[PDB]
Image: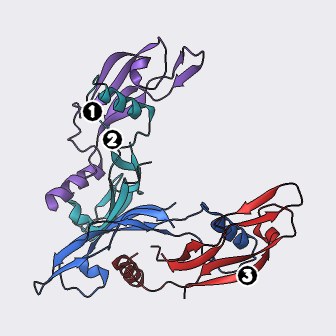
Chain colours: A purple, B cyan, C blue, D red
């Protein structure tokens, strides 16, 4: 499913909408694209049961980037975990 | 918590699966379906926020899928040929 | 835990005496209710655990439908319409 | 089947940890609810008998008794709210 791909966008942590005030920036990566091909027995049978008579697979992160630690303007440090995709896949 | 993501069971003949098997084997096939509107990860919260801000239009959203699969099903078909179905039926559903 | 699960069935499978080939997806509520939301439930759980009350799980909370799916309609073999109301769960809760 | 039962208990029988000599009348709902009021319960019963399948109606409080205040072996007053049934119903 090569249509399911990873895209990177350069953002400020403040663009994440998490309510933090900081100058930290990051490259945010996300998954998008089609998952029209069956990658498991389960999806094959889901299809067949349609052509016979939802739950379709989706392009999502299967691996996440490393933790990102940043300093707030309020002196509090924060760690974002599983906030950005490292690898994408149909699941 | 996306309570709408549920497991649904259907009793089928393995021949109902359209996999080409010639057997009398039957099984309870289970599949996952339902809504996953609620963000369950930092990643999904961010996607919701970037869509609202128009920096990334609503990307693959989380979907209701199996998080666990029933055990492998081994059987001999009508010609005594051995076959195994792996990750063919849902055991547990989750927004992923 | 209390969750909604579903099963594909034939209307005939319901045992209501209908003669039809129509099917449906029946959804139901099942699971335990171990959280006591009121003092009454906390007391029943304590009385039960201390054996001051004997009945298995005397009056404890049950996993039940708190909302129902749309009503099911179908035509039987005699070409008579039937509507099954509040026949399937849409949401489950410990009550 | 589903009825209210009133019994005389010591507050200490409740297992709330409070040391006291106070008592109370505790009323609870119990009994069978094998009457299928809704199509849903009719169906559950049929699926259980046909071994096709799961929780049928249960006898529960649909109304509660007034609050009960009680004194501890200390300077603190305690109050029990919705701790005793006043009316029962199969739900």
Distance of label 3 from label 2 (alpha carbons): 57 Å
Distance of label 2 from label 1 (alpha carbons): 18 Å
Mark 2 or 1: in front is 1
Say which element carries label 2: loop
The residue indicated by pointer 1 is B58
Front residue of this view, candidates D74 and A65: D74
State which quadrant residue B39 falls in. top left
Say left or right for A18 vs C39: left
Residue B69 picture location, percent across and down: 40, 53
Of all chains, the one bearing label 2 is A
Front residue of this view, candidates D12 and B41: D12
Of all chains, the one bearing label 1 is B
Distance of label 3 from label 1 (alpha carbons): 59 Å
Say which element carries label 1: loop
Say which element carries label 3: strand
**Residue shown at 29% from the left, 85% from the top:** C16
Front residue of this view, candidates B10 and D67: D67
Say left or right for A76 vs C20: right
Residue A91 circle label: 2
State which quadrant residue C52 falls in. bottom right
Residue A40 circle label: none
**Residue shown at 34% from the left, 60% from the top:** B30
**Residue shown at 28% from the left, 61% from the top:** B81
Residue B20 picture location, percent across and down: 19, 59
**Same chain? Circles 3 and 2:** no
Residue A72 picture location, percent across and down: 54, 16
State which quadrant residue D44 falls in. bottom left
Q: Are marks 3 and 1 in contact (CB under 8 Å)?
A: no
């Amino acid at each position: 499913n090569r249509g399911c791909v990873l895209t990177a966008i350069h953002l400020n942590v403040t663009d994440l909408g998490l309510g933090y005030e900081t100058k930290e920036e990051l490259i945010f990566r996300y998954c998008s694209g089609s998952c029209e091909a069956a990658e498991t027995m389960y999806d094959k049978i889901l299809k067949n049961l349609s052509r016979s008579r939802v739950g379709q697979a989706c392009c999502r992160p299967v691996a996440f980037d490393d933790d990102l630690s940043f300093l707030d303007d309020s002196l509090v440090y924060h760690i974002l975990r599983k906030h950005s995709a490292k690898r994408c896949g149909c699941i």
